[PDB]
Amino acid sequence: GTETVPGLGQRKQQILNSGGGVWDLAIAMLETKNLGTDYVYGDGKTYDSANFGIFKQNWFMLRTSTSQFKGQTTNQWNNGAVLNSNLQQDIKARQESQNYYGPDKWFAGHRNGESGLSNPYTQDITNYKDAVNWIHDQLASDPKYLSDDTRFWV
Amino acid sequence: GTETVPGLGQRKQQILNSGGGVWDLAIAMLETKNLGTDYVYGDGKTYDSANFGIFKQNWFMLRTSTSQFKGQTTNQWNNGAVLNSNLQQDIKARQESQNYYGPDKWFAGHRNGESGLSNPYTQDITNYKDAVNWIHDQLASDPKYLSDDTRFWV
Image (cartoon, rainbow over all chains, first blue to last red; front, side, top):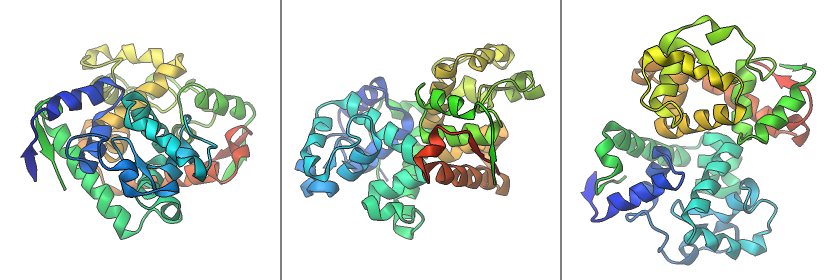
């Protein structure tokens, strides 16, 4: 459905002004209500499972597929927390990660980490991918949704 | 299958050093044998159908979904020819186009233009997507394929 979140429109514009596209906005919109990074640290997870930034990218993905973190170890997972305060780096990391894995494998590793890359096409990953695509379709339907306070949720 | 193409490794590394990811390399690899732009001008097409750059992006997609050509008209289609000699702009245009439409719609509009956006899941579009994914899998199977002269063709 849809809900109105006061001030969300300014944050959408900040994401688009910081290198994000509509597709990035759709992913972030699914992950948090406020397009924010103020969920609990690591979204409560640690090491390769820890989540950072507006997309809740996991550390496994960051350390294997971004210019900023490639080659870093599982033990260095707290390094990902800089994405909670640097929106430009957060967006660039997700785009690089998707351009490394391609969209199908990026979805799988984003959702199921390393085990997801072993088969991107299970139903659980499909459900997440379908939800992002529905949200993108809504955002792409009218330019007003790129700057108003409308949130599409699944 | 596979084939060896002299000079291909140089073009692979230029793509990966000019903003492109392995995902971009897979798409370009499907579109031309030499990762080049020296097919006939527009690939023999004109106006919204004309193709430019190493991905053979069409002018309809360029004018509707990139920052460089945003808002331009069908009649301005020769403006896309700059992509035939500016690889950085070529790659950035394709990545922006995909972030605007999302991967599934980008594939559909890349393959079938504006009408593809209305029917994005035809067998032909699916076949094209599956070809890119297979090619990406082959590139990703050994780091040497990112700099050697091996082409994977479908």
